Amino acid sequence: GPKFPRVKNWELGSITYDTLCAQSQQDGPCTPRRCLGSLVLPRKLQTRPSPGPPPAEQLLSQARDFINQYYSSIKRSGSQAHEERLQEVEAEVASTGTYHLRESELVFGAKQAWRNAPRCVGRIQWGKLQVFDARDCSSAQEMFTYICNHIKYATNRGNLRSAITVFPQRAPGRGDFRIWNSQLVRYAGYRQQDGSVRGDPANVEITELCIQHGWTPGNGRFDVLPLLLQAPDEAPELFVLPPELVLEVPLEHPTLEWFAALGLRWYALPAVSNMLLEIGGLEFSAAPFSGWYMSTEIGTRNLCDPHRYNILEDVAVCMDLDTRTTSSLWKDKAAVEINLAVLHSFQLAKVTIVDHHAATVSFMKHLDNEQKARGGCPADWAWIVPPISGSLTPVFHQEMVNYILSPAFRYQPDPW
Amino acid sequence: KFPRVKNWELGSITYDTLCAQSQQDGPCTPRRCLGSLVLPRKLQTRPSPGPPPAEQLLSQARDFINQYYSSIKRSGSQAHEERLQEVEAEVASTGTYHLRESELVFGAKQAWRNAPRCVGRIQWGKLQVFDARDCSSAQEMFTYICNHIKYATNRGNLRSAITVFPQRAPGRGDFRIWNSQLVRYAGYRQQDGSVRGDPANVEITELCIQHGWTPGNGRFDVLPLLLQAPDEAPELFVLPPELVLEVPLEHPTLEWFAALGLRWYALPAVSNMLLEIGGLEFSAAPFSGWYMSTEIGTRNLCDPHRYNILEDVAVCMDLDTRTTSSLWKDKAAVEINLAVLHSFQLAKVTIVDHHAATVSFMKHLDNEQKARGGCPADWAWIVPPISGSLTPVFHQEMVNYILSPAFRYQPDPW
Ligand code: HEM
Ligand code: HEM
Ligand SMILES: N=C(N)SCCc1ccc(CCSC(=N)N)cc1
Ligand SMILES: N=C(N)SCCc1ccc(CCSC(=N)N)cc1
Ligand SMILES: C[C@H](O)[C@H](O)[C@H]1CNc2nc(N)[nH]c(=O)c2N1
Ligand SMILES: C[C@H](O)[C@H](O)[C@H]1CNc2nc(N)[nH]c(=O)c2N1
Ligand SMILES: [Zn+2]
């Protein structure tokens, strides 16, 4: 039949063909010889620092494709404005080597980038994104102001709103605008004498970096790290987020009264700050974006991963489970309660959150929408299926095709 | 290039060089990844009415023979040289060849070892191989299958086994076991499209009935086998009840669980896959091991398109099924898997939970890294259907590719 990947849902027995992948312009890490789909960072997308200006020919092509996408989205392909805009970009790249996006083009691209994110399960919200333009930002201090406004607007006292702030694009031979921290909010990770870690092991390097740069460290398990902001060609400056702006939620269990005595907690705003936003060839090295948490991110990965807070054993001991034998499923039990505690605490504190069931169901709806609107949807199965109760959610039974579409959010090397 | 493989829990890194030995193409291409897909668009195993290209076959044959003699440290030896000459002599004159029992045994084990979707390959070296190539009828197939079942079951102390029927032959029909497993519970369609029993077995249940089987009306009615000898209509055979060991399900603390009347069989044995060794194809080669609890507790009993018992268990547990956020599904799932483990251990029947199982697979990855320079694994199938990140394999990157000997899917005979 159709000359495109046949995709099946084994629960409902339904079939679809992905024709959108034909639009992919960039190769992933797989080949007919072997599948590398489970690799977190295959060295492909990896936007490695490419200092010297990019091949005008290369950029022009990416730029024309994007502009075509833009005019198509407003239903004006082939129009005079479309052709003139095309001429304008080529002219500009011709005389300066690069070009700039109009306001509405940036907004469209930011949303398309989210829309094209293979690893995001919250894409049903893609059309609703507050885009803060900060391409005028000229200092590390101004980056801090912008970021604070982002946090304030997105947190909105617990009624979270998706948002993104776009700082100046990478320029010919000039320094990049960078946010060193992987997220706007991160708990410190203190390397101990015995070799262990206090706080979040995931943040040991950035914590040591903040210290090397003048931050006086605390000794808690949930210390909010300061931000290391870097304006072009300048060393990074240290900024401490005003406590009132970082909304947190103490964690308690709905029936296990002792859980609250554990003193656990998590922050409300999930905001990635280390990714690169690419649109029509243009590269925005600093463009933090945020939505709202899916309970398993906090309850399963952050709190239960071996290399994170690793609280599984502590919680099992409290539930008086048999932690000496795997077959007691003590790990599974503690994990469920820990996750329930996150959903409970967030609801109580009236902070936005979505469980893995609700989330995946909404993603199934998103897949339907996209099948009709674009003939497919790039999705990374391993990342879409939740870390717990995998086959209990609908996405587990849904085959998925993964591929790279631009605009996109890509990983980028650490500035240090 | 050789892929860098990382374990995000430990920080350890390795390089898979084994993938370089892959000679068969997968579904992926640089433009898009199709690793989450269950079946090949065609990778399958097309008909065999004509002889396979002498060149190709001979190529796969030499490779396999080389593999074998290497395994017994007798490479380049006299036997190795003469064995190669035999194979060539036979292919050249008949367009095919046959394997020696020892080679077949080596092939079966290698196929299991190369199976990317198998999480219990640490056991790959311990496999009882029943040579059934001297089988000429459905009736004989049935006797072989009964012995395999008696042996494998071993009164609850399961032993991994495989039975190999005649290889496919040019222009002649294949020997085939129509059922997907040697033990399957009937799935009866009735009234309003609903199904009594196992929905996954509706079609096969219907084929059996059409071939004279007197259907039952239960949720767990053990189906009969439809064994097919070359170019002949399949034959119906009922398995002796005392042979099909089953485990009644109860819960360690929840008294009411047993009242649900749930049960599952002890022997997981695939009988619809094809075994390929050195170019030769074995369309009927049933193999069995022992169950990992999540297969029964999570997929078979909880899949929405299977027994789908989640809600029932939830209501019995008096959970809040009004909303997703109460995690009633996750809670019932855990109790159901516990019950499965409890019940099998009570019945003294082999079973492995998903934690122990994935821990052993990790040791296997290590054993293989040192033994072959890598290990083909399918991450989507290796990670358990519940508590994914709570097991070590979730945090382990994997490379997937096709090595031979190999187990492959093949078209349904009807
Ligand atoms: C509205 C709520 C949203 C939810 C519930 C949601 C949920 C998720 C989840 C569960 C992940 C995986 C997190 C992990 O495993 O570490 C993710 C990844 C991702 N999301 Fe969304 N998302 C939302 C909003 C957004 C927004 C606004 C953007 C972009 C403008 C976005 C872009 C991405 C990207 C690019 C990734 C992958 C990043 C990486 O590879 O580390 N998401 N999202
Ligand atoms: C000793 C105990 C064994 C255990 C615990 C084990 C476990 C598993 C599990 C959990 C799966 C996935 C099942 C599913 O989700 O449907 C699997 C798949 C598979 N196993 Fe093993 N296995 C064992 C023995 C064997 C043996 C003896 C063979 C063959 C000689 C084998 C061949 C395979 C193959 C080919 C697959 C993929 C089947 C398919 O794609 O349908 N396994 N195994
Ligand atoms: N994840 C959500 N529920 S809202 C979307 C914004 C967001 C995406 C991904 C992460 C995980 C860290 S991945 C990284 N920092 N590159 C955190 C925050
Ligand atoms: N599964 C084990 N624990 S032992 C290995 C033998 C085995 C593998 C897979 C299945 C499931 C059906 S897959 C299919 N029929 N192709 C059944 C039996
Ligand atoms: C090795 C493996 O790719 C890795 O552990 C992946 C699996 N799936 C994931 N899925 C999500 N959402 N987030 C992750 O960080 C991961 N990690
Ligand atoms: C669509 C998706 O590939 C499918 O549901 C897969 C996922 N992982 C699996 N893993 C195992 N072990 N067994 C399966 O049947 C599946 N099904
Ligand atoms: Zn792939």
Image: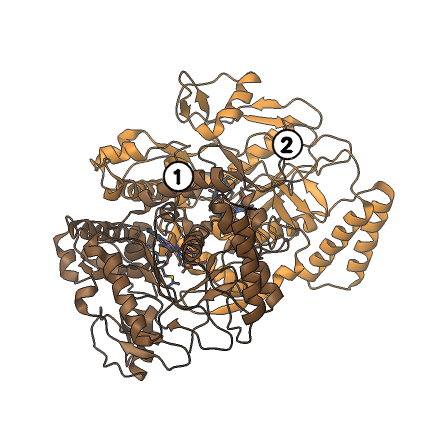
Chain colours: A brown, B orange
Image position, residue A246 (x, y; %): 21, 64
Q: Is mark 2 within 8 Å of ligand 4?
A: no
Quadrant of the drawing holding the N terminus of chain B:
bottom right
At horizontal 64% and vertical 32% (from top left) the residue drawn is: B176
Q: Both on one chain, marks 1 and 2?
A: no
**Which is nearer the eye, B403 or A181?**
A181
Left or right relative to B173: residue A214: left
Mark 1 or 2: the one toward you:
1
Direction from residue A413 to residue A325 in the image, left or right: left
For label 1, the crowd category at 10 Å Cα-Cα, with few meaning under 14, some 14 to 19 and many 20 or more, is few
Query: Badge 2 is on which residue?
Result: B176
Q: Residue A254 at what x, y percent from top left? A: 16, 49
Direction right: furthest residue: B93
Q: Position of residue A175 (x, y in %)?
A: 44, 77
Q: Where does the C terminus of chain B fall, quadrant-wise?
A: top right
Side of A194 where B154 appears, left or right:
right
Q: Nearer the viewer, residue B286 or A315?
A: A315
**The one of B266 and B366 positioned closer to us in this rendering:** B366
Question: Which quarter of the picture shows residue B135?
Answer: top right
In the picture of the structure, the residue carrying the numbered disc 1 is: A365
Q: Is label 1's Cβ within 8 Å of ligand 1?
A: no
Measured in 3D between alpha carbons, the distance from the residue under mark 1 to the one under mark 2, in whole angstroms, is: 41 Å
For mark 1, give the secondary structure. helix
On what subunit does the disc labeled 1 rest? Answer: A
Chain of the residue that carries numbered disc 2 in the rendered image? B
The amino acid type of the residue labelled 1 equals Lys
Q: Position of residue B56 (x, y in %)?
A: 78, 49
